[PDB]
Amino acid sequence: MEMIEKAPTDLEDRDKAPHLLLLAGIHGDEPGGFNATNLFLMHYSVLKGLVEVVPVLNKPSMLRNHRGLYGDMNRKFAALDKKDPEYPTIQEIKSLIAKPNIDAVLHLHDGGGYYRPVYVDAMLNPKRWGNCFIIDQDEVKGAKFPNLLAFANNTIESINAHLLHPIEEYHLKNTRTAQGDTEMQKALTFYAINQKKSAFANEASKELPLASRVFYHLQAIEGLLNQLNIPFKRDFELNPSSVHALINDKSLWAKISSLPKIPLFNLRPRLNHFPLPHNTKIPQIPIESNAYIVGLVKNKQEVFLKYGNKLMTRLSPFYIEFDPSLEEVKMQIDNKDQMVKIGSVVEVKESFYIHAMDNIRANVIGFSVKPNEAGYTIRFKDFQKRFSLDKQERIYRIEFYKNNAFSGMILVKFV
Ligand SMILES: N[C@H](CCC[C@H](N)C(=O)O)C(=O)O
Ligand SMILES: [Zn+2]
Ligand SMILES: [Zn+2]
Ligand SMILES: [Zn+2]
Ligand SMILES: [Zn+2]
């Protein structure tokens, strides 16, 4: 996991309001939480103070849509064997929580049903955790903001001013953890209370569609930020339609290794003969995105590209040495010569032509005449469209080889 800071543009403004640590994704099958932290990171600005964000605590489990591959990570904050696979991660998390710079902690979850204080039915009862705002105790002496109960009551009131359906009404849950809630005594927020941080958990119901879960998580975040007097902005209107559009953001991309950025959405469901660097374990292959919850994971003979719990495409890998010597290629684009950098996307209105290179072979994927296809003037009508990266059939791979090594890729997009 990674921690990402959301700070004011002026460094000196960091100490002028409180500091929140915002965490989600300790359970890998709770996408409301880690899509909310993602959207917070992408679309909000913190104007004074600081919000530190760990958008997904348990990324290996998120990648396999799993509650916890190594067990429940949210029961590992008390006793823990040093040989537990997550022991180092727990120590990193405790370190972040217990830093003197942190004042408050907000931990996001998705939970089944809808909590009610007395039993109604199977979906609505006190054993359920959905749509409630949780504290371990009413007060934490020594904290900058000791009145957890007041903060919670006000945060709940804020959320409840924006209910989508009345059944979704938020309720307070005080677990009184120090008084023998054996389970909660091993969880993250109790650890935070014991470091004299004001700590809260927000749980959105799993009965809700993802965009509604994320809506309630953002409402909780905004409610707590208002209580803390951490000033913020966001670049969208907070409603489920907007949230849906921002999760399904067609501007999202992924850059795998030194390859060109590819769009996250509307990829073909399988990409064949996809070059990946050899002798590299999948978790160590670099992958960048403008989102914060994107990754690669092995599944049988494929490598999945994941956006949270969403499967964006199935890579059928071609493991090969990535020779980094080739920096750029001379291409004619729409009659005009230019030096195109390896790893870029070039837009094409009409045509292109790759100038031949002594020791480099070009394969235009979807075009045919160990193919060498430099020296051909290529138009959209020359492509077999099923080789496109995208469902829209506009984006094609050009792969370069200095045999038997991969020298890089350029994408052409027909516009
Ligand atoms: N349903 C959650 C409750 C966690 C509440 C609080 N102790 C926290 O850590 O977030 C769980 O069983 O993990
Ligand atoms: Zn935005
Ligand atoms: Zn959870
Ligand atoms: Zn409001
Ligand atoms: Zn040149």
Image: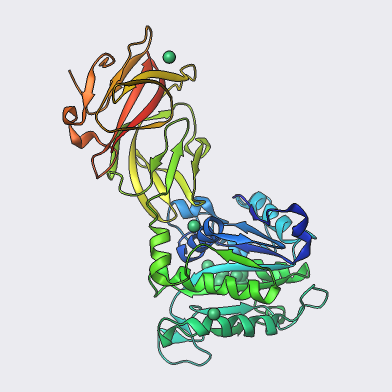
Q: Residue furthest right?
A: 142
Count of marks, rendered view = 0
Residue appearing at x 39%, y 75% in the figure:
207
Tell me residue 348's x, y (percent).
30, 32
Camera-side residue of 134 and 393: 393
- Which quarter of the picture shows residue 376? top left
- Which quarter of the picture shows residue 54? bottom right
Q: Is residue 210 visible?
A: no
Measured along the vertical axis of the image, is residue 198 above or below residue 328?
A: below
Please say which color scheme the image uses.
rainbow
Measured along the vertical axis of the image, is residue 254 above or below residue 277?
A: below
Residue appearing at x 60%, y 60% in the figure:
45
Q: 131 left or right of 248?
A: right
Q: 98 left or right of 54?
A: right
Residue appearing at x 51%, y 50% in the figure:
60
Where is ligand 4, by quadrant?
bottom right
Tell me residue 286's x, y (percent).
51, 36
In the rendered view of the protein, which quadrant contains the C terminus? top left
Measured along the vertical axis of the image, is residue 259 above or below residue 43?
A: above
Q: Residue furthest top?
A: 358
Tell me residue 170's x, y (percent).
52, 83
Tell me residue 270's x, y (percent).
28, 41
Q: 168 left or right of 181?
A: left
Q: Is residue 358 visible?
A: yes
